[PDB]
Amino acid sequence: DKENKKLLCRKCKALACYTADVRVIEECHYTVLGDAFKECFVSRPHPKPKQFSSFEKRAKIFCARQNCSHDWGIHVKYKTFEIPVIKIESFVVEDIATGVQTLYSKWKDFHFEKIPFDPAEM
Amino acid sequence: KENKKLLCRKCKALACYTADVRVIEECHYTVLGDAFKECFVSRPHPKPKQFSSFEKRAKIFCARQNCSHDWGIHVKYKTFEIPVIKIESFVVEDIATGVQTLYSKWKDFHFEKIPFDPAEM
RNA sequence: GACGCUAGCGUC
RNA sequence: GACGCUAGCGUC
Ligand SMILES: [Zn+2]
Ligand SMILES: [Zn+2]
Image (cartoon, each protein chain N blue to C red):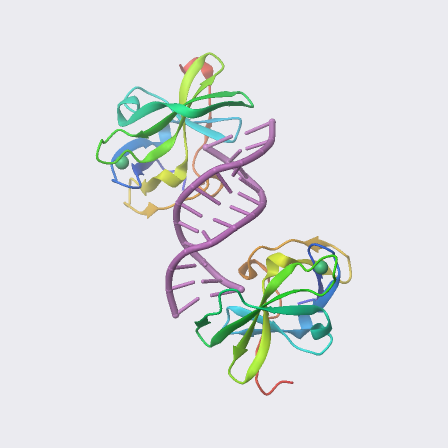
């Protein structure tokens, strides 16, 4: 399905983002656009920051719900931007039209409309 | 479908053929024939366990001394002491072409899976 | 053996 | 984050 879909925290089922705001960096990593998502996660300086490829691993990000704090991914410095990078294993994908939920472990198995990251959008 | 060879993934020594492979409970895989018994050695299992219709009695390893790659287990099934192998320990070679394939789980290997028959040899 | 989990470890 | 490896752990 290329239809729009929701991402919920796999632990607490809180809404995180929608597939329409997802951008793909280097056909491998996934980020979310908009400020509404920044409220849904909290970050902490990474216990072991690293530089790889085109990223600066600076922080870990977690579900903002203090009762949850589920690991969602990392926060990196990419080019001139500081953006979050998420892993799908921390989320449940819900089809908006039908409500069907899907548990992915790797992004290669989630087939949705993947918009390439565009710097001009930010 | 076509017959294929299984080589030890570490030392590439031939172990068996898909014709001699039988399936137990559509989940476990054993090898028929006496040629295969020359290809593995056994060692009593560190954590013996009974599960389903199996008594986990030993681990099995490649008989080549410079290899001894872990190949699976050896179990007591019904009235038989038979080996049970895991595909991750082997590389599958096609007979006609020599194309090699590395499988990690049996569910991804598609061939004519003949069910184990206690009457069959 | 099938499968599940955790934990580190390494790579760009 | 993506991938790889290891090591145990749990289930029949
Ligand atoms: Zn949550
Ligand atoms: Zn060997």
